[PDB]
Amino acid sequence: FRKMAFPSGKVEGCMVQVTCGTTTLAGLWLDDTVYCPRHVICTAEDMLNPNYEDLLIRKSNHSFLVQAGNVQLRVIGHSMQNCLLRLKVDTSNPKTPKYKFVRIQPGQTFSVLACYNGSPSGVYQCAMRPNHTIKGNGSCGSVGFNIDYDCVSFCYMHHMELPTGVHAGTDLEGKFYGPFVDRQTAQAAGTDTTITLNVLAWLYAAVINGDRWFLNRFTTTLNDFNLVAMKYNYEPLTQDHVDILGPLSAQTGIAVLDMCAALKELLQNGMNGRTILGSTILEDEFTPFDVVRQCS
Amino acid sequence: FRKMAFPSGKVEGCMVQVTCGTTTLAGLWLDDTVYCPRHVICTAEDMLNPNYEDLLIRKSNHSFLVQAGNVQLRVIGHSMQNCLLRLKVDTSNPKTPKYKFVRIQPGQTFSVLACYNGSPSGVYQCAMRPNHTIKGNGSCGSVGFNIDYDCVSFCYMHHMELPTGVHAGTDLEGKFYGPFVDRQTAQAAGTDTTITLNVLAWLYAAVINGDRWFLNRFTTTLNDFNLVAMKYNYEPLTQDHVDILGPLSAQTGIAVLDMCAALKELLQNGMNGRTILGSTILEDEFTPFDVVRQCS
Image 1: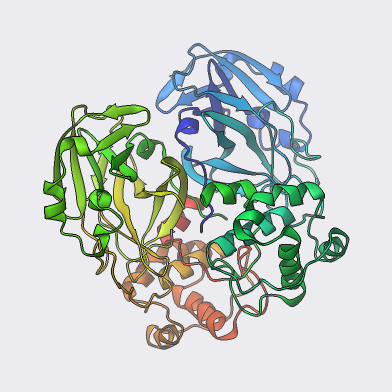
Image 2: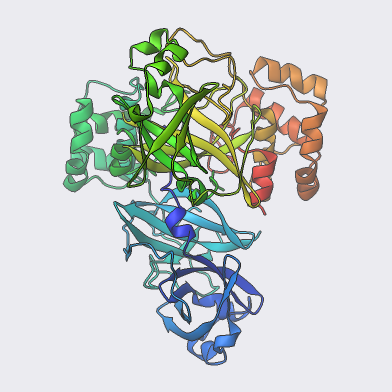
């Protein structure tokens, strides 16, 4: 069992390099528009307290060097759309896939196409944290996506590293996830928690894959489990979460509350130097939907 | 810090579905040739003791349904090339990237484009184990690759799951990694070991990323470390491995043998319930080259 991203081909065809001043970062070229973080116009000094409207007036179309692979695109318009820079180019992308802009939820996973060394360089899978951060030099940024049947659902664009090393960004409409702004100040993240629903989902995956030792013959309750969860900084389980785990519960023959009892035991008793799916930690970056999609 | 694969776009354009009988699996369409595991011609019963030459004579061109996305390719020839089925089609792939066939070495990493539910479905990074296995239902197989500048280096194609759940396959010439054959028999893997060089490389990455607690003020020697390594089923360190870690040693200011002393301590003393890069286990699936490529 492994953490796997969606194939990145369709997103690769949309990735461009946007340069303004000394700042070079990644953009998304869809039809005749390029999207990138608006702080591309900021010197690493404007970032302290940026008046973006003011800084943008100082910019013209020629302030922006947009490079699609090894073609320089001619920029014929610029505007601000929330925290995104909206760039109009003279050519519409012939590799534009069918796409939607979705705003994902805390606990939900997505694939990331990471820009390093001035181009699309790597791909990995991650989860939006309950505190709206991302655990994701020469970074030129990154695009988050899921592939929903025939369509690319763009959900994330990287903007900032916070002083703690955790990342913040926006959806593709330019609206930040969580309480964050694109300003180099003392923005503290909310206290993070483990995504319970995902941990249970991954436990089901372990059972599918042969790891059974953590199973016991006790059950629990939503009220009891959530006390334990509160203590261990886990997300509270709701009835919605239980209903979601239905298919996996049927597949394994282990009732969701029985699996919660196994988890409760694992939090209080540890793992005694054992492994679940080659892991000594409890993994929370697989949704039930990711588990279903892998087996099978 | 995260395990990331190469972007998969160039490999996605080469992936086809090859059907023979009830067996459907993934092929690689390059120019006018499709490559897939030869056991596509076997019923899950021929697999016990397959005479492949004999089974192939019974097949004709019409025995093979080759589907590129949603185009059925017409197969105009078939032959066997080691453990690969070599299929000749009437159309050469217009999405053929620049590519090489490389045979990688134990300890070396590669990206995998995994075929699930009858199409390219997922992407992840992995290492060839020292015992020539892969830690990688509805599996239709998978292609292993690195992207070496402008060129795709194909290094792996999945063939078999062994009775222990570990995977075996070939390079793209059809030659198995390790002592394995494409036959459903009692093939036991060699005893696996941890890739030392990669563990040191990842420790350097931890130091780059701020984790420093495991550093001490002792050094060790190749002869001393290798006794400890033997005991803990780690690969012996060679002078080649030390020279390879040079750039990372210079970057961090930590001499390779000093880092070995930190590792030696970690093997004998554990981690006392601490973490390195969010991990309580020692990670061996990043080469020095992967670490350099990420930071930066």
